[PDB]
Amino acid sequence: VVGGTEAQRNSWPSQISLQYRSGSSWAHTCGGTLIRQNWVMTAAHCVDRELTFRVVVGEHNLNQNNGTEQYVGVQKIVVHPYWNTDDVAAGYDIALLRLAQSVTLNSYVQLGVLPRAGTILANNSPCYITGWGLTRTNGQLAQTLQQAYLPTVDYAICSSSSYWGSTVKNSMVCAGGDGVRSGCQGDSGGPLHCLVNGQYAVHGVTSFVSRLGCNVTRKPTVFTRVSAYISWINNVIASN
Ligand SMILES: CC(C)C[C@H](NC(=O)C(F)(F)F)C(=O)N[C@@H](C)C(=O)Nc1ccc(C(F)(F)F)cc1
Ligand SMILES: [Ca+2]
Image 1 (cartoon, protein in one colour):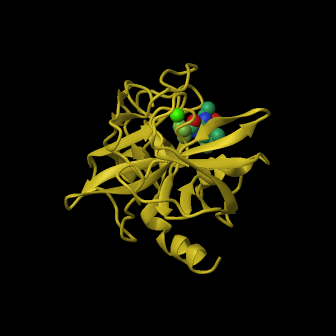
Image 2 (image 1 turned 90 degrees about the vertical axis):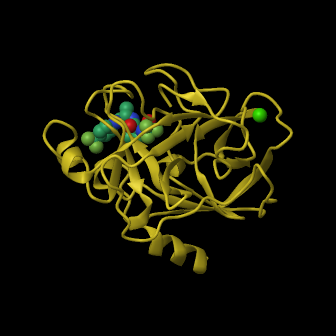
């Protein structure tokens, strides 16, 4: 997350690390949201390479033992049927991972809350992006879960010539845009948390930044808008 602040051990407890095995060891690739005791929403894009993956729930500091981590292997990766790998801009950038075990719920390991279907955030909705991704353009991944305040820019503004143009769809949330904060590489798959009737609901799954850099003026961070995809989620969990 560029322009972030270390989050607390328990501010965002649906946040998981997707890790892939790296010869001898595991490595952070992407984030995700634990949506059932054994199901993690992430990006289709994260799980695009043929690599062995584990999920880590209870993670705050990657590099150090927190006393709270549960490591569980990914059993099944269900990508959106319509996702084309060579076109993020078509949308559909979402995958559900069934975990080999169901994980223990406790203060560090909770279910993320999903929006209702159809739900569109209003231009300016208070939202937080959370992740271990790069803290600079061409920089380095964070040791400790970070957050940045990332307020929504709606379809109309986001699809003008000045901001994104046709690259962004209404299947999509663009939060941010201010030159200072946004997502960046390694936050992908992660949750956008936005405040709705006293709850933090997950409204986006982190998709893309400009080819040019993470924190770029008039290029918000783009997230798969979860409320579009609710029935697909429910169906994949119901039949699998
Ligand atoms: C493309 C994916 C692997 C996503 C990758 N996303 C991220 O790093 C994250 F976490 F911010 F979501 C990204 O934006 N990387 C930059 C460097 C990129 O290639 N951006 C980008 C790609 C395609 C377009 C498009 F759709 F217009 F072709 C626009 C920007
Ligand atoms: Ca750790």
